Image (cartoon, rainbow over all chains, first blue to last red):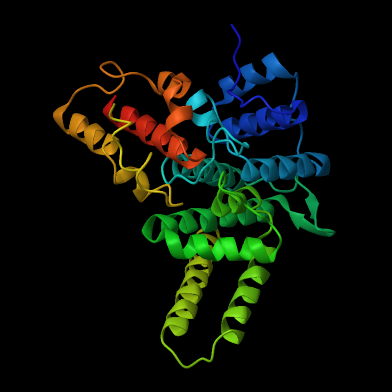
Length: 244
Length: 81
């Protein structure tokens, strides 16, 4: 019997990293037997002892997981960010995958906070600065919550947020043709929230400089943008206060 | 024939893969079947068969249509089973 996960069959290293983050997601969701079976079927050993190397490895795995999407059957594998075989902005399977990733991250955080043993873990590096693995997981979960509330805003009103993300990508030089969506491109490159913030700032600056602040439509547009940012900050602060 | 008679595969040409599929005939037929109680996986072809069929390559315009149809079919089968 061969126990493994479904992959869209891409690069070898990409598939290996995808299997690794899928095993990590299973370990988070407490599918210990399935994760061990898939590890013994693919590699040999993955989970080690808490140390700086393990923290860096789990940080890279979480980055790959928030950049991609887990799978198990072709139904879940069709949502992996491909090129011409899936990932076309859907508020159903993508939402379920995102909520499953969030549940796994929350369960892992709750377990590692309730075990009451943090002296065994170290502090990994992030952008040249030393941060804790708990803070890194909290930041990843905050990014996931921002993505899911952006998906909710898309399901509510898709045109405004879609045009905003498209303008941001066009300003940051990320041309998207008629095969993919700017929202899906942002979900794939979610690791650039600081760049997306500057893109929105530049978009608002262009909107204010191309007008004459004397109408109502521009005020409504800037109010909607401020409300989107308000929802982002609100869900971030809510998750942080819940994890505090 | 239900896919061919849809109001999105050849009538509308927007870029929103949300309401464009809901404003068709396939979603309405699936909702009627779900409300009636007929199984969508045994009394209807599967998503794999619908994807492997050659009618998609001749009736499609962008990948958004195919992805949204596949996701809706999978969600309906999951909520019916």
